[PDB]
Image (spheres, coloured by chain):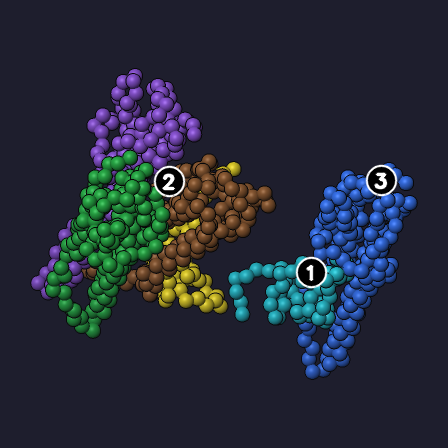
Chain colours: A cyan, B yellow, C brown, D blue, E green, F purple
Amino acid sequence: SMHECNTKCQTPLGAINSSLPYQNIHPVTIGECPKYVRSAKLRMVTGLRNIPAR
Amino acid sequence: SMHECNTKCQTPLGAINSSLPYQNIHPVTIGECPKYVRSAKLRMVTGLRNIPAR
Amino acid sequence: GLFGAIAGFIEGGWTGMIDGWYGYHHQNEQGSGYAADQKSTQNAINGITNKVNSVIEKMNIQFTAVGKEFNKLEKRMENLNNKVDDGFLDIWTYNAELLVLLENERTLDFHDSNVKNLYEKVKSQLKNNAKEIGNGCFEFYHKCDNECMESVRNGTYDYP
Amino acid sequence: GLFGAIAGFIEGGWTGMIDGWYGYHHQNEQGSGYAADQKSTQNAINGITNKVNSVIEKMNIQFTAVGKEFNKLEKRMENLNNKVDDGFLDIWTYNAELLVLLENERTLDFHDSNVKNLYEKVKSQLKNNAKEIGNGCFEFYHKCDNECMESVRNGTYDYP
Amino acid sequence: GLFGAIAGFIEGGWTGMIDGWYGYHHQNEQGSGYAADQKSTQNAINGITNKVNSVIEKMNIQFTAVGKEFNKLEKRMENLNNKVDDGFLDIWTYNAELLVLLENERTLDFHDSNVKNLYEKVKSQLKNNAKEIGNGCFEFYHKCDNECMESVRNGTYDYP
Amino acid sequence: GLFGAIAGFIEGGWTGMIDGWYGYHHQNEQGSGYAADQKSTQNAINGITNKVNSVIEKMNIQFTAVGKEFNKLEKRMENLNNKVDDGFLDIWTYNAELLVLLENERTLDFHDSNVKNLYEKVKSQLKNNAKEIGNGCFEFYHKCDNECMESVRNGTYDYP
């Protein structure tokens, strides 16, 4: 349903307000969306291996 | 303008989702709204007089 | 202050207490630090919570209030509607601000009272064992422990 | 991991470190505390920030991708369209999970590298004045200050 | 208490003292008993009687007020009548119950005031002839009679 | 009253006070006279000016309000006009005399409070250098001049 929201991306499921490179929402896009990928998790590590020494 | 939102109170300016006793938004109300009052501030103190002693 | 404790004989509050609205600062050989008086802090909190509840509960929630139309030969009934709505809005705005003003004055006087009654309880405990130095502070003559310092918080303190 | 420092010769990481990813813990007569080695931590943060930027930069933002209808005598061109859309989405999903597994391994290997580089710079610096105990811990033979522990952080330390 | 005498330094009230709201419990070798302080009791009774008369007199008696009929084409003037009757009933209930809550505190604070005012009046007679022992109880130094107990009631006993 | 100085142990006020609401009387060998305590007078005046402004400013100026005519078949809307105008006038009379009694009560306690706050502040300065003689009057042991009297006025005189 239409609402007075405004976003750089639209898909059939809803609008996407993100700066993440990939998305798994819907392949059909309108305007500047993230690239569609079928994966359920694409999480990169930035820190090191957590071993609390507990 | 009408949107797919739901609230216990409506006024001509917009819907009010609050548990505060008073409001100063608009006199015309629909449903379970706070009491309309012309005041710009009805802040009551609960703490003591702040003197940081800096 | 209406009791002369807050901004009076005690000049200012301590930012180092976070545990309550009233507390003490010790100066034992075992160290220093801030520690709330639980009883006066809870009695003040329950008093002020019942005050917050009372001013919210005693006025009822507003139901649907909607303005009515009046034609070219009903302008007396329009002016009846107008002065009813305006006159109700006057008395609700009148009672709202006067209740806030009176209860804000009272709240600060009630906190000033709770600092007074706390200081005077410590005076009735310590008595001959300490003198008034900083107006709020009590130099011990016998120099007792952190356990005896806690015995002044709960307020037993078994020494003349 | 691939360098035997993280989960290896140092048994586990310290939760008392918050200042940086790699750091030391002194046990002087001046007391104890966790203090990050800034140069190794910041160089790792630059290496991680550059990889994080790179993998986001290399994909270009997906413009309007709209579905195309084909009639009852164009089902070959629908099967060309569907094969093209599926085959690109296959390859792009494979590229995304490839670089996630590969670079997450390389990240843990890179941090494990930086912890052995942190240990070997301290071993080559403390030399004949200290021995290994807990594999990471260096008992001094002369007992020097927290200023001299800072001299091992910055990597000066003027005594063989 | 706002003055810290009722439920404060004096722990509780006496069921054996029935002659007034305040007074003193004498203890002698001649015998023990209760005796009201007529001055503080009567000034409190006059102050509370004028206070109770004030709010009763101030709410004037409601004259004849009945329901009005309106036909099928008079629903706006019926709902103006309803808005007027309900809005007056809101403000009269609100003002009555707030006045009760407020005045009930001011009465209890006034009684707590009169106990501290009576206590400090006896303290300013027994300066160096007695010491405080029970938080309300003064033990004498020279052990004076029932006449001396009555002299401390009536505003005399000007001993050092 | 509520604090026990005004009509309390300081039995009456001085007609020799003309510069302020509070102050001290001279009894030194340099001669008798009166000198107002400026800080207690000004803080009382600022509190009184704020409550005087608050009660005047809060309810706005009453604009044009005139009588309305009603014909022989408009007796219901005439008695609605009368019920509204009388009912609001009941509330405005009731609210005016509520605030007048309550603010006059609190004003006399506030002034009675300011005599406590000034009395205790001088007693905490004098301590062991002067006794109590006239309930207000504090007789000096060592004796001192009019400049040493002025030191007790201005908030200095820090002698055990």
Residue corresponding to mark 1 = A20
Report the Cα–Cα distance between label 1 and label 3. Answer: 46 Å
Q: Is residue C127 visible?
A: yes
Residue corresponding to mark 3 = D157
Q: Nearer the viewer, residue F95 or C49?
A: C49
Badge count: 3
Chain where mark 2 sits: C
Q: Residues within 10 Å of mark 3 (few under 14, many from 20)?
A: some
Tag in front: 1 or 2: 2
Residue E143 lies, in percent from the top left, at 28, 44
Q: Residues within 10 Å of mark 1 (few under 14, many from 20)?
A: few
Residue corresponding to mark 2 = C4
Mark 2 secondary-structure assignment: loop
Mark 3 secondary-structure assignment: loop
Chain where mark 3 sits: D
Residue F86 lies, in percent from the top left, at 16, 56
